[PDB]
Length: 105
Image (cartoon, rainbow, N blue to C red; front, side):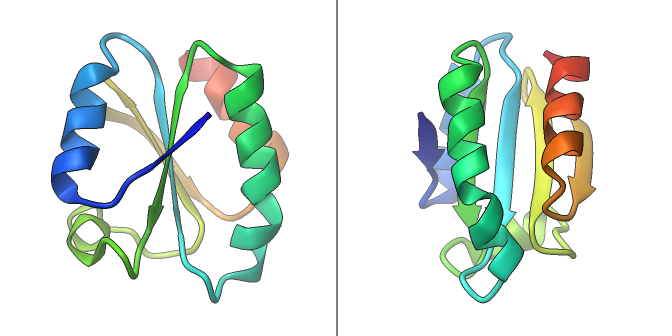
């Protein structure tokens, strides 16, 4: 299951309720084709890795969160453990996404 985030408070609350778990956040936009192409694979990871928390943030819904997160290229994947950012990259690269998860979990 992928968390759909629709405020900065929900984002912060999610990072807090994570406990010690890896949190993976997909920042995407509706105009970003590859963002829409990777979305099912993103959902698959959330079903596969029930141990890891997956969130989606749409940058035009959550402009504050998008700005604060210093997002530049769509999609961007950020990774958190205990409220701290422990990884980031951009681009719809499935293999890299999963590899990154396995390094951080």
